[PDB]
Amino acid sequence: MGSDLVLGLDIGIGSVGVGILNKVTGEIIHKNSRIFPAAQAENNLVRRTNRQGRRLARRKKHRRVRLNRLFEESGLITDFTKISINLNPYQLRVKGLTDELSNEELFIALKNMVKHRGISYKTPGQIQLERYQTYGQLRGDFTVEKDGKKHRLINVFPTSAYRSEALRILQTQQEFNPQITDEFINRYLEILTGKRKYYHGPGNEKSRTDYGRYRTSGETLDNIFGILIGKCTFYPDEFRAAKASYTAQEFNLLNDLNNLTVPTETKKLSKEQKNQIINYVKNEKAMGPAKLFKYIAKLLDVADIKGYRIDKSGKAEIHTFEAYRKMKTLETLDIEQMDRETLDKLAYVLTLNTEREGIQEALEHEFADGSFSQKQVDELVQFRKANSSIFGKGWHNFSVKLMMELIPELYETSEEQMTILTRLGYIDEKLLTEEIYNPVVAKSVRQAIKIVNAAIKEYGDFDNIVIEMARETNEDDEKKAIQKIQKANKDEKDAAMLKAANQYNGKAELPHSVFHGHKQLATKIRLWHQQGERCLYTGKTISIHDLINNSNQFEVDAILPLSITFDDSLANKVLVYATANQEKGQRTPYQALDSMDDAWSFRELKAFVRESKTLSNKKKEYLLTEEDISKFDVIERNLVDTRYASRVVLNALQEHFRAHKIDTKVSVVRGQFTSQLRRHWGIEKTRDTYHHHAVDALIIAASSQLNLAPYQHFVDTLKSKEFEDSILFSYQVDSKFNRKISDATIYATRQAKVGKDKADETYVLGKIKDIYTQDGYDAFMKIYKKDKSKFLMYRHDPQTFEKVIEPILENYPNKVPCNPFLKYKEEHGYIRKYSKKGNGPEIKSLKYYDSKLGNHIDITPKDSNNKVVLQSVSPWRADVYFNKTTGKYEILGLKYADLQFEKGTGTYKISQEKYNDIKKKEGVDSDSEFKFTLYKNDLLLVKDTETKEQQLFRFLSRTMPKQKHYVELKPYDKQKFEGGEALIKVLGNVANSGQCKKGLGKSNISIYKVRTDVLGNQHIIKNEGDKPKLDF
RNA sequence: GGGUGCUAAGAUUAAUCAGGAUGUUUUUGUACUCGAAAGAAGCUACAAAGAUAAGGCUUCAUGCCGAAAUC
DNA sequence: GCTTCTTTATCCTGATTAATCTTAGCAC
DNA sequence: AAAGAAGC
Ligand SMILES: [Mg+2]
Ligand SMILES: [Mg+2]
Ligand SMILES: [Mg+2]
Ligand SMILES: [Mg+2]
Ligand SMILES: [Mg+2]
């Protein structure tokens, strides 16, 4: 090509390694690590989950706001201030079934029913009220001992049952009350039972939201998943065709038929021979690949035909125009009256839409007015439901338009698609990623593109841009072993489905009716087959009759919880009874089994799992690992995204170096080659630091021009002492506001004297959720040994503390530690609060004075006698000032929670008044000059004035509000400090704990902000502006 | 040998929507403790009602936005 | 003031669209 | 991982 320099890229989810070198000389021209922690984009799972949770709560709250207006307009209640909140609504929901209720009694019964409306895929009040009476509790997920055994209940009931009940209640009230109109009953049942459709989403005509049906643009779709249909591989503004469309069925077969080799004089079929094979299968009612190959065996010996698509086992495959044949079995319609485009569109709607309303609305809106009658669409919706397996197979990679350009050529040429398409025929990173919905893959892509752009303008274009790719070379033996594993996987499902059918019907296939609204049945049945038809936490057998007809009773548990592992694979999944998944909670089977009331023992499972031959190896490893794993310790999704991001860029480059015709070669390397060259070559990848990314990339760049002094020189320059300390680093700064603001925990406070306090102080409460776990007793003892007066029971109920709790710690085992409280309960059941008659309630939790309230967010109810707070408030940015008078620096701290939505405007901002506020509390003189703002991962040089010493750090935040001008810093060259690292004299060693927290408000110290381009070229930025930037 | 295209499967995962049951905390009621009661205490449990990222929107409702990306 | 060290909410049900790797069968 | 009060 033009010049002599080859760039290498090692693209990851949070880093892209960079490296340039002369193909000829072997000199290394540039080395670089670009870092942008993926942790922030994977947070979007946190982001979706909370957004959806916010909508369920909003609508549950609105369900009772809606019921308020219903009650006013009916004239039943106007004044909602004297409504009592201490009646028993569950007793009124059973009383109103036969006897009259007060208008306010009725409001209480309906309001309570609306707050828990049940699932929707003896009335419940009666069952609830009797759980209240015999067990003293209704809600949640609790244990009950019956006839010697322990069972588990939950407050889950079907919405249809709440509907039946409310209908009976309001009807008998209608006997007694004349204001209970039929419209009142109807509109309440809408509030009660009303659900939005999954293909509509949020909003209404007035409330436009681009999350749902009624868009901000003014358009209102029929199905919000229509706009997510992929686009054509070649005509990129055309949507793709349904796999059940005619155009797709014709193209698929045609391309199949031109891919076989026949004994004909051409070795390939003719235009005429094709046309009646199409005509043959299109008019034959029964059809499969075998019957088809039996017929061109007639149209010419079947075993002499070659080139057919193969099955996992080997039972050859070919297209059959299956969708068209079974559509032709419609009676109210004919599948032949319709031209090409009205059958392709019928496939579009029947593929996308899955329910009556979605189908019925699409046909009206996208077919001419008189194209279908009520009985005709009646059959189509029954036809679609009876054939969800055919219309759930998705969408072709091609649009209809492109296939129309190809289809006649496939009739004519005997060429297959590819040879047909060939015969006829800087990068904008934002447009490249405009329609990729994976913020992790999308970000690593833009980071990689933005690097090559900057690499060209500082170095001109390249001869080669090399990209490491996570792909596999395999020889014959490995390959066979893959498809045997892939075969055993499909064999296992069919074996499971067959065993499911025999034990349900006796027949060998299961009716389609069972899979409606339970599309996941196949995988559940597969798990059910792996587990020997047994729930591995309770030990009860699971019968497909319950699994299909009472499918509520079961849930698919993540063995090692997703909160901790993020393992969504089949090996991290079992099918268990619902109540056992719930009690297991966020725990492994090991952590949870023996603690569960309605469950096996862990030894009985340790038995069954290895006595079992159906369970996977990986699945057994997960079911039994005694590892106290948790959320804060030191996955597959990361590999998916590396390949996705690496591929997207690689293709986006070779497209760029073709269409604009610069012809920079674009090559590729695998990890198996680089990782072993690293072993064969010298480079020793060092510990826990970002240097290895730049070296990874250079090894990538070298692996290409390896077909060749210079081979020597390059590896010399690589393994040299003066190399690792010459690598440059550039981090992506995070300036985004309105991130997660604090911890989720809602903390109570009390006034008390603790330790060396003789004036009352405000204390934040903690709570031991369950004293009967060892983690609960462990926490108990730490507090007990340090200060028993911390437990509020010690202070406000000393009878229980010294007459009930203290004796237990005397008379119970404690040891392999064990929990004395749990032993007691194995004896007497739940520790009861002290009383004279044995009357007291049970004890599960103990709250304690924890720490003094410091920095917080105030969420105190107007109700409350004590403040309620959120804590661990997260920072946004730090504004650095200097004060000429004192000579010292003054660092202000901004947090996400300091910005808010301004009421009148709706804008998200901080006002100058409150900003100038934070200025005074932080110790910043009003007559000091702003200098530069610091955001996350901005770099800083901290220069010592006393000595000549200086050091470069990267910023994390302004830390510890009480200690003014205190900031926490992270290293320039790696992720974290180990602890005790030497710094400049004035700052001293970083704390041995690991966190570098230092106050920068001293007298002899110079600090400058530093920026880098994405290549690691830094430039000092001593002053930024006159005033802090606050534009919103 | 890499790259890529059509198809089918196997294995992973991403985006988005509709829902359930909790958990946290406030207040009240009841039980428990104290008091002769009224009550007190706010521990401990159940229930209900309110709040549930701080906080906002307008179109009064199957109402809408608020933890990603934009650097 | 400087360092240490405790602390940190979740389990599911139903659905659609998309991507990546790996086997296959054809092909520039 | 990092907030920030506890601890000295
Ligand atoms: Mg689970
Ligand atoms: Mg705790
Ligand atoms: Mg009281
Ligand atoms: Mg935190
Ligand atoms: Mg603390």
Image (cartoon, coloured by chain):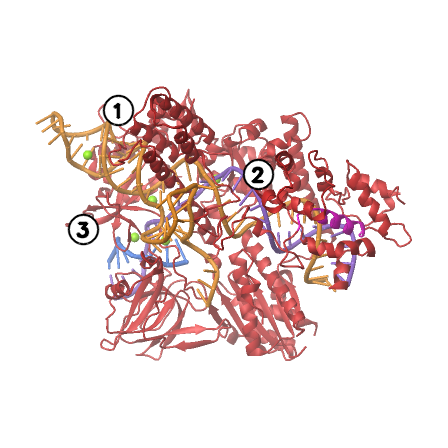
Chain colours: A red, B orange, C purple, D blue
Q: Secondary structure at mark 1?
A: loop
Chain ID at mark 2:
A
Res. A628 image quadrant? top left
Task: Reply yes or no: does residue A591 show up in magenta.
Answer: no
Location of residue A347 in the rendering, given as x and y in whole percent from the top left corner:
66, 44
Judging from the image, mark 1 belongs to the subunit labelled A
Position in image of residue A807 (x %, y %) = 26, 32
Question: What is the span of residues highlighted in magenta in the rendered image?
Answer: A241-259
**What residue is pinned by disc 3?**
A756
Q: Relative to residue A782, is residue A446 depicted above or below? A: below
From the image, tell me which residue sits under label 1.
A838
Helix, strand or loop at mark 2: loop
Q: Residues within 10 Å of mark 3 (few under 14, many from 20)?
A: few
Residue A583 visible (yes or no): no
Looking at the rendered structure, whether the residues under marks 3 and 1 are on a common chain is answered as: yes
Q: Is mark 2 within 8 Å of ligand 1?
A: no
Locate residue A513, reporting x and y percent.
Answer: 61, 31
Q: Nearer the viewer, mark 1 or mark 2?
A: 2
Q: Is residue A852 visible?
A: yes
Marker disc for residue A355: 2
Tell me the residue at 29%/26% (across/down): A102
Task: Establish whether ligand 3 lies closer than 8 Å to the Cβ of label 1.
Answer: no
Work out whether A946 lies above or below A770. Answer: below
Q: Return the x and y of residue A797 as percentages of the image width and height.
A: 21, 35
Q: Chain of mark 3?
A: A
Residue A313, numbered label: none
Q: Quadrant of ligand 2?
A: top left
Q: Point out the tag, 1 or 2, that comes first from the N-terminus.
A: 2
Q: Are marks 3 and 2 in contact (CB under 8 Å)?
A: no
Is label 3's Cβ within 8 Å of ligand 5?
no
| Most distant residue in the right direction | A265
CA separation, marks 3 and 1?
37 Å
